[PDB]
Amino acid sequence: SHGLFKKLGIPGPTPLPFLGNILSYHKGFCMFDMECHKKYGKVWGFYDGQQPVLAITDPDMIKTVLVKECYSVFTNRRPFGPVGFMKSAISIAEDEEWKRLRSLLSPTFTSGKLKEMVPIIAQYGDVLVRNLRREAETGKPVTLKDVFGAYSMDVITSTSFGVNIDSNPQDPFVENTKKLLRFFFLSITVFPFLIPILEVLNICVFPREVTNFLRKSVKRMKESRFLQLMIDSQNSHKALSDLELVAQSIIFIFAGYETTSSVLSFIMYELATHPDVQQKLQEEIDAVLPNKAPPTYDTVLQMEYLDMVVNETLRLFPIAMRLERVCKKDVEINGMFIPKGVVVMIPSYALHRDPKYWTEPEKFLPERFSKKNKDNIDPYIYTPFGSGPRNCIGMRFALMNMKLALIRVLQNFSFKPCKETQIPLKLSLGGLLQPEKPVVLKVESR
Ligand SMILES: CC[C@H]1OC(=O)[C@H](C)[C@@H](O[C@H]2C[C@@](C)(OC)[C@@H](O)[C@H](C)O2)[C@H](C)[C@@H](O[C@@H]2O[C@H](C)C[C@H](N(C)C)[C@H]2O)[C@](C)(O)C[C@@H](C)C(=O)[C@H](C)[C@@H](O)[C@]1(C)O
Ligand code: HEM
Image 1 (cartoon, rainbow, N blue to C red):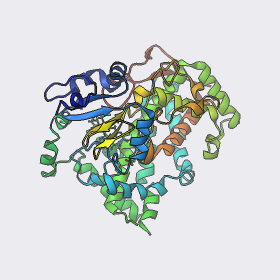
Image 2 (image 1 turned 135 degrees about the vertical axis):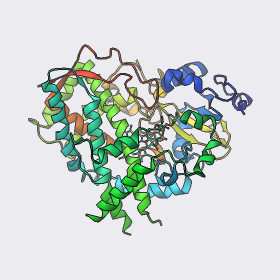
Image 3 (image 1 turned 90 degrees about the vertical axis):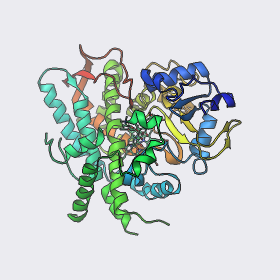
Image 4 (image 1 turned 30 degrees about the vertical axis):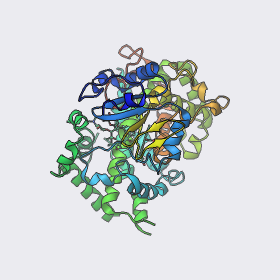
């Protein structure tokens, strides 16, 4: 079983009997991918405990798994139990049930329905520059994740649950959300055979107290009246449960919160270490919005450079680090055989820094994304939101949301690196991609 990749002739780091290669994860997922890439080349295999994982690297082979053979063979992500009623959530859902849930949720993510939402999101822009200005008054350097955390939290909770929070007020609905996001898992990887053993017991990774509260909180709101567009949905190929509704709303918190605020801390870090880029971006804002005008959907999508800054940050810091897809059946793909059961992984972080596709990959250069160079960028090497039918269904919201907050904060302030800033940046050698040390900067009002 640990002889699968050898048998098939695929190089890979050698596994220990039960742990597979999980002890190599001590250096973080990113450096693990980078080293394997540089060492084993185009394709490599390893083991998360017992699970064969096959990393792939060819834009062609990637297109086949992420777009072409999506519905037929590479439909699902790694299973993860035990999840109870959350198996109804779109990111957890598998096969035809996922197909159905995805179809029912598209209409909720169109640009337009999103344009109809920028106002809701704009409220929280003010709230963010205020908290930011308050910390700037003090005269001391700012830990940005306090405010970007709060901002990301507020935008995501608002849009998914109705409630309109200024968290400031940090003991109503906020406290359940905090308790939901941050929760054994080491063990689950060694023994996926222990997952069925736990689901029988009704043991679930999402805490029942909170889910209940959240389940109630939507029943109340559904009565006293993304949430709306899902209500819209329940009136009219397929149906859509009340329990499935709340499940998508919880999932939106999980997907939108930490990714968004992480990206903002990174984006801010780079503008601060690259003053001529911050300068040019503020120059752009001041041209499209003459004197601190309210940001608009139609306005944002007219901002060339900003889109290049956001994209180049995601190139160097793709929060999900990898894309995964389970292989349903024996497949021959662009002249390579993949057996059923294997997890095919796309190493986004590593591919984003491959000297074959990017010149000087370590350096931050928004130019890569300029009108000139952009059309040679491979859409299967650059994947901060994944690709195909099972890509990030909230990609467009997230970009709009980040940009909104970027806009408001940037026209009002300016960012120098101070004393306690990390130079150069260290990355969280742990979970989802994050600065290893909270980003701290000097925030002067302009
Ligand atoms: C951004 C895009 C998405 O990210 C991912 O899928 C990556 C690739 C996973 O890493 C996968 C894949 C892999 C290989 O890492 C890349 C693996 O090592 C881990 C265990 O799971 C994450 C984070 C998972 O792990 C869990 O996230 C919790 C917040 C912390 C928890 N743990 C650390 C306490 C961990 O189990 C998990 C289950 O998918 C989170 C659930 C809630 C989701 O469905 C959410 C909404 C996601 O779809 C997502 C955030 O949008
Ligand atoms: C920087 C911000 C964000 C990033 C980088 C991001 C990234 C991702 C990535 C990489 C995936 C996996 C794609 C793949 O596997 O091919 C994904 C899936 C998903 N994302 Fe996001 N996301 C962000 C914000 C959001 C927001 C704000 C929402 C909700 C509005 C959201 C909702 C979802 C959902 C529901 C899925 C699973 C889709 C499916 O399984 O069909 N994301 N996201």
